[PDB]
Amino acid sequence: APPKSVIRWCTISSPEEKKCNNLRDLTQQERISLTCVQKATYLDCIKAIANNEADAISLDGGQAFEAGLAPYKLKPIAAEVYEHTEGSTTSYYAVAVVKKGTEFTVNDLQGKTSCHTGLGRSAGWNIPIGTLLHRGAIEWEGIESGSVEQAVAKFFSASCVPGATIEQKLCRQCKGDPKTKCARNAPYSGYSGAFHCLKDGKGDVAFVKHTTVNENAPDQKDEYELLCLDGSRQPVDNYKTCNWARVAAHAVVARDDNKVEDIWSFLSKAQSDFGVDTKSDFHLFGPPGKKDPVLKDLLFKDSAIMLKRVPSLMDSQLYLGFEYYSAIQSMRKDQLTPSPRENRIQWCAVGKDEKSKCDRWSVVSNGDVECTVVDETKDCIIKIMKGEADAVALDGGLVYTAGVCGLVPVMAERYDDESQCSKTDERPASYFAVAVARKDSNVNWNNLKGKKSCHTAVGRTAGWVIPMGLIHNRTGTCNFDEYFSEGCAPGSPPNSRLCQLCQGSGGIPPEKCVASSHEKYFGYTGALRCLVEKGDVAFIQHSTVEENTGGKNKADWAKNLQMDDFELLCTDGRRANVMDYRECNLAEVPTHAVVVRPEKANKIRDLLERQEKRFGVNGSEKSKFMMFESQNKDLLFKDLTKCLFKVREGTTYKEFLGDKFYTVISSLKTCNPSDILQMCSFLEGK
Ligand SMILES: *[C@@H]1O[C@H](CO)[C@@H](O[C@H]2O[C@H](CO)[C@@H](O)[C@H](O)[C@H]2NC(C)=O)[C@H](O)[C@H]1NC(C)=O
């Protein structure tokens, strides 16, 4: 029985409850319905909805955490948006600002004074407080050696804070009367009084809501400037790159189940009809106006423009940002039982063949290099960015998605020899993608359709990702298994048209179209064989021909063969001569890469540099183990790797790839988006 439900919204107070029923009537005259409740607290409202006792409730980031925590583990279904300038606002950046001419960054701040707005409030407490806890700054493991209050003393020497139930070394530079000071109500805080701290010099370090140094006084600028977590420091409007946190913007949670989208539809509709534009008696976002503190941001935040949707996958750990998460993880959510301080490197293993590979190391790395194995190679991307994982060595495409998520290359591979590594003379390496056409052949990029094709596998950059990539920009939709009359592409569907060329099994079980050892048309040469025996074209490397031609591949087929029988097929028709890989290649394909996070970079390279020669190719302990080798199969690290040098500092995946590469990789996956790739992406436009 098809879609048609009732959405029971969760409340907090009676006045907000009353406005709830006041929509009833419409929910009624409309398809999806409602049933409003009321809970004295939001924790109750959360445990309520959780136990299917209710549908959903819109929350803040400070709560959205708690809401996402177990056993609740509630999902963020849709955020709220606002009117500023930058873009289509969906957050509120958490920064920090001090006076110009500062002789420190943060690694030595274990003594200077400070200044907050109040305790347990974001930007002020929580955030910098948590960021510092997780950045080890404040030697702290649990309140019983240094409470959130205690620890302050053995970190600070001054803090202007309204929290005085226990500690004093966090109650100093607050201006005013001798009995009205450390009170949350003292005008020496909020966003201006604490901003008055650096202004009236009463406190050295002070971090508040961003862009307040604009609301306050656009004029006098550089007397104050923002300070980054990565050594750097910058000007007034330099927050979108030098802000402590990606402080979110009120979202809408819910459990994780079938009864979900209806929650999206009973609202989006409760918007398009009865929204800010509604010509009725309701303003679903609260018209910008003042009111009674009892009735503020009711049902939904009053200072909102509209509500934007949030991806299926999207969790707390993700929606609110890493920063905020890392910050608040430093708290009493757990001191260090399910979240230790293992500063040392670890790796996203992807396979039992890989985990243990990583494990094969973990003994001979005495902690210097840890492990966490995975199932889908895409688990890597989320884990690292989740802080759970540290690094990863992946293929071309995965690098794209990653970079969109915020992760980037830090130390790429080398496929020639270390005898061209530790230097900055000729950085990248030449491996090209070519459209191998036959000598007397018919084919060409202009009559390439309806041709029998030969791909290595359903996924290798040169042997697949690129063809389909270029192809996309002239395919209608990604009906790749609906272009060539047929072909072989080991890994494509069972009885598909794309496996038709696959000569499958060598004998025994009819393993056709397998990206397995058991395949005959597997790999570059396999797919080349394909061109020779069946196909009208084969997608492979620049020097894939040379490898066999010249009397090199001494097989039942190649024996004779001269590349004087193969030709390059250029995207413009030009039947280029094999030897011109440069002037007739499909794509200049990059080498793999260790994509990681913007905060552990230069030092992660180090870790790999330490172990580099320790367990590297020309390495010393070659009698113990290595790194690239693994049963003689590419495990995380391809086996055809010698150097793995520290790349260029301050680059980007877009740069790492190349326009002619990014361009097509970006616009290929456009043709068919995906979860991870979708979540990271909507977060790009925050
Ligand atoms: C195929 O890729 C893109 C996407 O279809 C085509 O055009 C875009 O290419 C890049 C984005 O992927 C951008 O740099 C271009 O500016 C963009 N085009 C426009 C009008 O903005 C591109 O033409 C195709 N590739 C080639 C080589 O033609």
Image (cartoon, grey):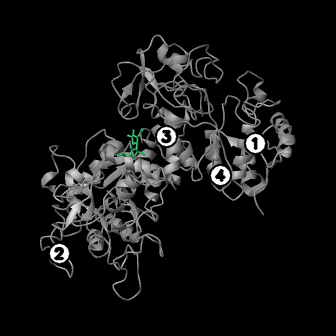
The amino acid beneath tag 3 is: Glu
* Mark sitting earlier along the chain (3/4): 4
Residue 617 appears in view? yes
Tag 4 secondary structure: loop
| Mark 2 close to ligand 1, CB under 8 Å | no
Q: Residue at x 18, y 67 (%)?
A: 622
Residue under circle 2?
553
Tag 1 secondary structure: loop
Q: Nearer the viewer, mark 2 or mark 3?
A: 2
Residue under circle 3?
684
Residue 187 is drawn in which quadrant? top right
Specify the quadrant that holds the N terminus. Answer: bottom right
Residue 202 located left or right of residue 314:
left
Report x, y in % for residue 542.
Answer: 22, 59
Q: Residues within 10 Å of mark 4 (few under 14, many from 20)?
A: many
Q: Residues within 10 Å of mark 2 (few under 14, many from 20)?
A: some
Q: Which mark is residue 41?
A: 1
The amino acid beneath tag 4 is: Leu
Question: Does residue 334 sit above or below 159 in this rendering?
Answer: below
Q: Mark 2 and mark 3: span between their CA atoms?
A: 49 Å
Q: Nearer the viewer, mark 1 or mark 3?
A: 3
Q: Mark 2 and mark 4: span between their CA atoms?
A: 58 Å
Q: Which mark is residue 74?
A: 4
Tag 3 secondary structure: helix
Residue 137 located left or right of residue 570:
right
